Amino acid sequence: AVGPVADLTITDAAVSPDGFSRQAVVVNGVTPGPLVAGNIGDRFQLNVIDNLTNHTMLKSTSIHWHGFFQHGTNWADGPAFINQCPISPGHSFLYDFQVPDQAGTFWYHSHLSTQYCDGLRGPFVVYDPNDPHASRYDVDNDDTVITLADWYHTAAKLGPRFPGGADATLINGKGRAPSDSVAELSVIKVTKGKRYRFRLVSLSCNPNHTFSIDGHNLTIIEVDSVNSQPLEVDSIQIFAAQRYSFVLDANQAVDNYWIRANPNFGNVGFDGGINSAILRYDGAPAVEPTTNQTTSVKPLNEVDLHPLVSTPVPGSPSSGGVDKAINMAFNFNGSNFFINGASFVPPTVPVLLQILSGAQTAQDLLPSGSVYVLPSNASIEISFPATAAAPGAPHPFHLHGHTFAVVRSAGSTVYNYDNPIFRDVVSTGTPAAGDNVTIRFDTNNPGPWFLHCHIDFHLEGGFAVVMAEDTPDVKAVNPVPQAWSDLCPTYDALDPNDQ
Ligand SMILES: *[C@@H]1O[C@H](CO)[C@@H](O[C@@H]2O[C@H](CO)[C@@H](O[C@@H]3O[C@H](CO[C@H]4O[C@H](CO[C@H]5O[C@H](CO)[C@@H](O)[C@H](O)[C@@H]5O)[C@@H](O)[C@H](O[C@H]5O[C@H](CO)[C@@H](O)[C@H](O)[C@@H]5O)[C@@H]4O)[C@@H](O)[C@H](O[C@H]4O[C@H](CO)[C@@H](O)[C@H](O)[C@@H]4O)[C@@H]3O)[C@H](O)[C@H]2NC(C)=O)[C@H](O)[C@H]1NC(C)=O
Ligand SMILES: *[C@@H]1O[C@H](CO)[C@@H](O[C@@H]2O[C@H](CO)[C@@H](O[C@@H]3O[C@H](CO)[C@@H](O)[C@H](O)[C@@H]3O)[C@H](O)[C@H]2NC(C)=O)[C@H](O)[C@H]1NC(C)=O
Ligand SMILES: *[C@@H]1O[C@H](CO)[C@@H](O[C@@H]2O[C@H](CO)[C@@H](O)[C@H](O)[C@H]2NC(C)=O)[C@H](O)[C@H]1NC(C)=O
Ligand SMILES: *[C@@H]1O[C@H](CO)[C@@H](O)[C@H](O)[C@H]1NC(C)=O
Ligand SMILES: [Cu+2]
Ligand SMILES: [Cu+2]
Ligand SMILES: [Cu+2]
């Protein structure tokens, strides 16, 4: 792991995670990027060095630290043209923030256009020396992070606008495509008799994955950085950008067991060892598993997840029993997505910079129709009714700057105002099911926060809005460093081909 104080150098480089060589955006020479780690309470000073030279994958960059509240450091949140102008090539930019009140599994990724699909993404763990789940496991380290990524042979700006699946699912940076049946698989080592806290992070740009491990059950103890009660499952459907910690007890026979991550579309299944990695017990031969997948009899259901500690749902136990309720009506016209009639187009002046320059109302803030001003210290309910008008479901939505209660989950008609899980990325389900996924949060974090589909190609097509929270306190609460103030003039000074 690198961090909490570290350089992250961004370059273009040839990679071959599935035996197919292609130029990609890499972090400290690798994609997925290295694990960044620290402890609860730490100040992170992540110096992002932009040494990119390839305009097609973008020479500029901006990095989001996914899941962190960024209270008082909204300028460091990442979304290009919401919280900063991008970092320019040949420049560095210091993200400097604290994590006083969170611990769990996170990740970092480019939040500029579709650049994270081209490889700028990696895991991020904040450890708790007093973790309430510590007694459930023996090992929790760099080697118990499991990343899932969709991998494309054609670059994000060069392929279809909305790809119909990846060429390969990568598990810990490796996996197979049909073009190379013998590409090196990832191996995750376990010692028989030891218990492992596996931190499963979806770095996916698009597909979700149904994760399971042959012959082993899993005990979920964390959901998007929120400690949960232990939930035993035998498979996990994980959506783009979500995280789970699960405990695996390595108490089976010394052997090789298939790790499976089946995408919802693309090359589905396991022919030739695609969508697979290897769980290898110390002492097992260095060969492929020959284990068989068994039917999931205890799949994860989100409604079965509950916080480990008592966590009150904002507002009052009835539909709309909050200070402010907002419904998000989805539309799509073939190239662009819309929320409540507006397709998001990034403004010239980042939303935070607009607020710093005086714009405090929806009327003054750009882009018009995409910014929702929220009152301070208020309960907010947002519903995302699934509709056929918005193809590419299930759409996992992410709210920046907050965790939220999932009062109603996908595939459920129940509203849980008592003990629902809190998380930061939620599937908005499908119209076939009549889904109306509904979340609640409190506004105790002044700043503009992006709320968007985390299928990166959909974000790109405008599937996003901004929650402009407590605009009158934003400037005072979020003092910006000189380096941040320098970003926009430097970016705006660039030749378009240097962007
Ligand atoms: C900036 O970034 C962008 C986006 O990433 C990047 O864009 C690439 O742009 C190029 C040119 O337009 C695109 O090129 C196409 O690339 C196709 C895929 O090539 C791969 O496969 C090649 C063939 O593979 C086989 O053979 C080898 C050995 O013989 C074997 O190992 C394999 O198993 C397999 O059997 C392979 O040669 C190639 O490897 C080269 O390129 C990579 C990438 O850098 C490099 O790492 C290697 O060192 C090596 O140089 C690669 O693995 C290719 O099929 C295609 O060629 C056909 O189409 C053209 C159409 O014009 C025909 O005219 C031509 O005759 C071929 O039939 C073409 O070359 C590429 O797809 C884009 N990349 C992506 C990811 O979208 C820019 O290049 C970047 N800028 C800079 C300066 O790097
Ligand atoms: C993972 O969790 C699953 C679900 O809880 C466990 O499955 C249960 O496993 C036992 C086998 O150990 C099954 O019961 C046995 O069935 C056989 C054959 O029918 C019978 O001969 C035995 O007397 C015994 O009753 C049980 O049916 C099964 N439950 C299911 C599938 O719903 C599984 O064992 C757990 N795996 C591990 C590695 O702990
Ligand atoms: C999804 O849930 C939302 C929030 O409850 C529903 O929106 C409300 O609908 C009623 C009509 O029954 C209106 O009076 C309210 O103003 C709506 N709330 C808003 C706009 O915040 C919505 O209809 C549900 N959608 C589906 C498809 O069930
Ligand atoms: C969809 O709407 C966008 C934004 O309003 C517009 O630019 C585009 O031409 C439309 N696309 C199609 C395929 O009709
Ligand atoms: Cu994210
Ligand atoms: Cu989407
Ligand atoms: Cu985001």
Image (tube, rainbow, N blue to C red):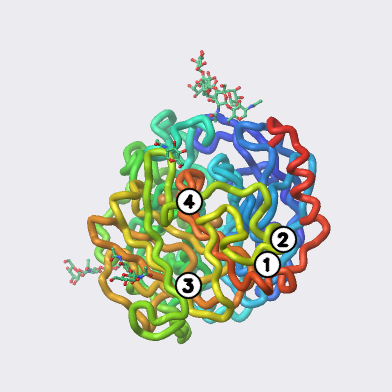
Say few, some or many: other residues with alpha carbon within 10 Å of mark 4 (under 14 / 14 to 19 / 20 or more): many
| Residue named by callout 1 | 38
Residues at circles 1 and 4 in contact by the CB criterion of under 8 Å: no
Q: CA distance from mark 1 to mark 4?
A: 21 Å
**Amino acid at dot 1:** Gly
| Residue named by callout 3 | 404
**Amino acid at dot 3:** Phe
| Residue named by callout 4 | 148
| Residue named by callout 2 | 3
In what element is the residue under mark 4? strand
- Can residue 43 be seen here? The reply is yes
Say few, some or many: other residues with alpha carbon within 10 Å of mark 1 (under 14 / 14 to 19 / 20 or more): many
Give the mark nearer the N terminus: 4 vs 2.
2
Q: CA distance from mark 1 to mark 2?
A: 6 Å
Disc 4 beta carbon < 8 A from ligand 5?
Answer: no
Say few, some or many: other residues with alpha carbon within 10 Å of mark 2 (under 14 / 14 to 19 / 20 or more): many
Pinpoint residue 139: horizontal percent, then vertical percent.
Answer: 55, 68
Q: CA distance from mark 3 to mark 4?
A: 24 Å
